[PDB]
Image: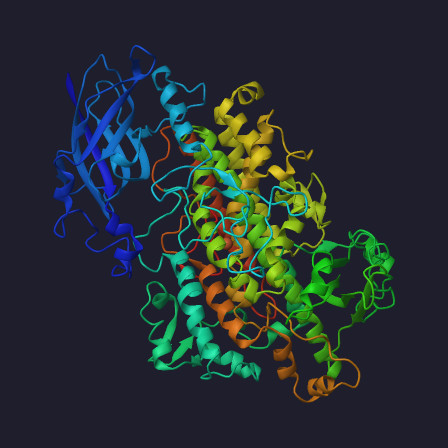
């Protein structure tokens, strides 16, 4: 024989678990970095605890399968390695192997040790005339009894599903079969089974009828992407709804641990819903704060002295894990909030028309604006005569002081723009306005000035039917005003728009278009692409922690009594309205250039840098996003073409073909007959599909997510709901608008209690964990032994670092006013790198928060 030398790196559960790690939380990657010696439970791993068994890649047994070595136990502790790193522990193991058994390509592992551990890697050396073999594992290994068929890990090498090494073919297939899981059964914590189900788990019909919520997906009225199957028992009152639980399953390895408490952000969110909200609600159902803001100064005091609570309410939020690192305190009565970047230079610049318009290009929701093609604008609604008979903005509403073009000449010269929030809310408005909320369906028209800035020209506030449903829109239109009560009216008009925009952003731009729509791709990938497949490795970093934050959203955010329903305009109709909007979702229109063209914000042009020409040059989201889109596309093209020799080779790949078919027909299965799905008959289609997935998971989510507190941490700038209609004529509220307009604004928008909820949640959502892995050429360890892919990944990051410098440069260009605004807030949201915390920058690989 020979002895093959193995090095196993693993991490203990205590080093990664929230419950244990609450006493470990300030400047991590550290602490004499855990080498595995003096606190030392490392001896427990040594005797008859953990067995590893190598599987030959080149020598088969009687019936095709790779030859098994001898199950071998960990024989010793390695105290130090130059590459060790925090929280890790290393073990030496030596394997009996000969020439005649060939080359290992996989291994089985059994944990007999009761407590699960996180296996990081195996390195094998001293194999004659062959280099070292590396296994990247990154998986939790539960007790061996729990399993039926052992945990298996493959070496570093990427192989197309000709399945390469013949002795390994059956091992590759069987593990893919184990991951699919059969389709029945209640899922358990230690399981790694990926499957699909509809969104039937958000409501709570056992609590009553008013807690039931419609099934989303699997029907034509409310189509939806699928989510991860959790197979709990159904509810008593409804066989089609899944019963609620405080713990939701996701396939183990999709839930990431952290070395630092304070990086456990989903745990912080869960605490805000469960512990913090009922406590804070007790103080309003009490007394110790007034239930309403009375001035703008009272809102600003949130970031100064904070808001005063009593000791025992604030002593029950001061020592909770994670939240004591993200909440401030002055002694023992003040809950305080960090000042949002929007007011750091100017307290009042958000009120400006310039800033209002600039946030449509560079704000939290910079994706919706479109170029006005024809005039007035029109609705896509079926047969009511605002749709059948348009918006009520006329041509004489739009002649202020700037140009004196006709409406027709501004349209000709691409100078008129539209923010249309009319259609999604319109069919639900009567129901919405029968509750505590009072809302309008809005449209706004914007004009590109000669200085390259945008200004709002008209706001249409539309209502549905004083009598009827047929006969269309009851609309009022409002015009900019500099002074008098008319400016206060105009400011309230803008508030009704932003309230529409905030809610659309939350449910559609953020929840639907990134979180919900990405989840079926994670499921399809794991069920059908082996860990060894090139395309699995390309896509994998972009899925990190997404099923985790989504499972928490189902539990705490988007559920029947939850945060979004209590905080935002659409209320109890929030999620189902986003299913209505999903009717219009098309995969290939999510590609940044396609999106820009569809909204008329760009035109096709070969002489321009990225092949498109921008109507509106200073559109910060778009100009910056186009650099990042191209860096992603180039990376994915170079990668894809490393592996697929021809279009036939891709057509022959059974794992890719099965992946895509199940994606289209099951995961986004309500859209299975749509003609725009790429077939996967061409390498170019694989490039485009992968580019769209990575764009979505990385920069699109970053752009739409990390500005939420910096722009909307002042509730005055991004209100989430409205609760009064416009003061009319000779009202007592109109007169109140004359004498005390701050109080009239405050009475229209989100109340104080729901403001505190909104701020606490979006402060968490807008934070980067310290162990975030960024686009900025980052990966976890050493994912492949293919050096051509490593070099190509290297070029991807050098391109990203060069793009970061180009973007910083643009922020210092005085000509580019939309990048900063009157609010002097440089657009850094698409800068790839970031440090940690409430940073208005940084593009994570994945939807991680
Ligand atoms: Fe998010």
Q: Is residue 65 left or right of residue 124?
A: right
What's the coloring here? rainbow
Q: How many marks?
A: 0
Outermost residue toward the top in this view: 62
> Can residue 787 be seen in this snapshot?
yes
Q: Quadrant of residue 793?
A: top left
State whether residue 338 is above or below residue 54.
below
The x and y percentages for residue 849 are 46, 54
State whether residue 328 is above or below residue 828.
below
> Can residue 628 be seen in this snapshot?
no
Q: Nearer the viewer, residue 240 or 569?
A: 240
Residue located at (21% from left, 34% from top): 7
Q: Nearer the viewer, residue 757 or 452?
A: 757
Outermost residue toward the bottom in this view: 739
Q: Nearer the viewer, residue 499 or 843?
A: 499
Q: Is residue 669 left or right of residue 85?
A: right
The x and y percentages for residue 612 are 68, 43
Q: Quadrant of the N terminus?
A: top left
State whether residue 349 is above or below residue 648.
below
State whether residue 219 is above or below residue 508.
above
The x and y percentages for residue 738 are 71, 87
Residue located at (53% from left, 27% from top): 658
The x and y percentages for residue 511 are 55, 53
Outermost residue toward the front in this view: 236
Q: Is residue 494 left or right of residue 191?
A: right
Q: Quadrant of residue 587?
A: top right
Q: Is residue 523 left or right of residue 472?
A: left
């Amino acid at each position: 024989g020979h002895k093959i030398k193995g090095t196993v790196v693993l991490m203990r559960k205590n080093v990664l678990d929230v419950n244990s790690v609450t006493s470990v939380g300030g400047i991590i990657g550290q602490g004499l970095d855990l080498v595995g010696s003096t606190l030392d439970t490392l001896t427990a791993f040594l005797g008859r605890s953990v067995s590893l068994q190598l599987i030959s890649a080149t020598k088969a047994d009687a019936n095709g399968k790779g030859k098994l070595g001898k199950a071998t136990f960990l024989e010793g502790i390695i105290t130090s390695l130059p590459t060790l790193g925090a929280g890790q522990s290393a073990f030496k193991i030596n394997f009996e192997w000969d020439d005649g058994s060939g080359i290992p390509g996989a291994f089985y592992i059994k944990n007999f040790m009761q407590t699960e551990f996180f296996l990081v890697s195996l390195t094998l050396e001293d194999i004659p005339n062959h280099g070292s073999i590396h296994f990247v594992c990154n998986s939790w290994i539960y007790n061996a009894k729990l399993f039926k068929s052992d945990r298996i890990f493959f070496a570093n090498q990427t192989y197309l599903p000709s399945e390469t090494p013949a002795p390994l073919v059956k091992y590759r297939e069987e593990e893919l079969h184990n991951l699919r899981g059969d389709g029945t059964g209640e899922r358990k914590e230690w399981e790694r089974i990926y499957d699909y189900d509809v969104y039937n788990d958000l409501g709570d019909p056992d609590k009553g009828e008013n807690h039931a919520r419609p099934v989303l997906g699997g029907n034509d009225t409310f189509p939806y992407p699928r989510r991860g199957r959790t197979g709990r028992k159904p509810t008593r009152k409804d066989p089609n709804s899944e019963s609620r639980s405080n713990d939701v399953y996701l396939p183990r390895d999709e839930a990431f641990g952290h070395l630092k408490s304070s990086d456990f952000l989903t745990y912080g969110l869960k605490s805000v819903s469960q512990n913090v909200l009922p406590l804070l609600q007790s103080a309003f159902d009490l007394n110790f704060t007034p239930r309403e803001f009375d001035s703008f100064d009272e809102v600003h005091g949130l970031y100064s002295g904070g808001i005063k609570l009593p000791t025992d309410i604030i002593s029950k939020i001061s020592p909770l894990p994670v939240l004591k690192e993200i909440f401030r305190t002055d002694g023992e009565q003040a809950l305080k909030f960090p000042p949002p970047k929007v007011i750091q230079v100017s307290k009042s610049a958000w009120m400006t028309d310039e800033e209002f318009a600039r946030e449509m290009l560079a704000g939290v929701n910079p994706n919706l604006i479109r170029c006005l093609k024809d005039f007035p604008p029109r609705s896509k609604l079926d047969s009511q005569v605002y749709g059948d008979h348009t918006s009520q903005i006329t041509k004489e509403h739009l002649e202020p002081n700037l140009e004196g073009l006709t409406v027709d000449e501004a349209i000709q010269n691409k100078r008129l723009f539209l923010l249309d929030h009319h259609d999604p809310i319109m069919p639900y408005l009567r129901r919405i306005n029968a509750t505590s909320t009072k809302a309008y369906a809005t449209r706004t028209i914007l004009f590109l000035k000669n200085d390259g800035t945008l200004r709002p020209l008209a706001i249409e506030l539309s209502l549905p039917h004083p009598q009827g449903d047929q006969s269309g829109a009851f609309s009022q239109v409002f015009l900019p005003a500099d002074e008098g009560v008319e400016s206060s009216i105009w400011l309230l008009a803008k508030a009704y728009v932003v309230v529409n925009d905030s809610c659309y952003h939350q449910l559609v731009s953020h929840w639907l278009n990134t979180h919900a729509v990405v989840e079926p791709f994670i499921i399809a990938t794991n069920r059908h692409l082996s860990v060894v497949h090139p395309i699995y490795k390309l896509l994998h970093p972009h899925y990190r922690d997404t099923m985790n934050i989504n499972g928490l959203a189902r539990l705490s955010l988007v559920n029947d009594g939850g945060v979004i329903e209590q905080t935002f305009l659409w209320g109890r109709y929030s999620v189902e309205m986003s299913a209505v909007v999903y009717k219009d979702w098309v995969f290939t229109d999510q590609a940044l250039p396609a999106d820009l063209i569809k909204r008329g914000m760009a035109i096709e042009d070969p002489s321009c840098p990225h092949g498109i020409r921008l109507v509106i040059e200073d559109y910060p989201y778009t100009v910056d996003g186009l650099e990042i889109w191209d860096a992603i596309k180039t990376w994915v093209h170079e990668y894809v073409f490393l592996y697929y020799k021809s279009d036939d080779t891709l057509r022959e790949d059974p794992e890719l073909q099965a992946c895509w078919k199940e994606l289209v027909e099951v995961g986004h299965g309500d859209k299975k007959n749509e003609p725009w799905w790429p077939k996967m008959q061409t390498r170019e289609e694989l490039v485009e599909a992968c580019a769209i997935i990575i764009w979505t998971a990385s920069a699109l989510h970053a752009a739409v997510n990390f500005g939420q507190y910096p722009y909307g941490g002042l509730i005055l700038n991004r209100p989430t709901l409205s609760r009064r209609f416009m003061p009319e004529k000779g009202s007592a509220e109109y007169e109140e608008l004359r004498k005390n307009p701050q109080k009239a604004y405050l009475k229209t928008i989100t109340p104080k209690f729901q403001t505190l909820i909104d701020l606490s949640v979006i402060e968490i959502l807008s934070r980067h964990a310290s162990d975030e892995v960024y686009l900025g050429e980052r990966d976890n360890p050493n994912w492949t032994s293919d050096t051509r892919a490593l070099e190509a990944f290297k070029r991807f990051g050098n391109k990203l670092a060069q793009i970061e410098n180009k973007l910083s440069e643009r922020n210092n260009d005085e000509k580019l006013r939309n990048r900063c605004g009157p609010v002097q807030m440089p657009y850094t949201l698409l800068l790839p790198s970031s440090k940690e915390g409430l940073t208005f920058r940084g593009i994570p690989n994945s939807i991680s928060i």
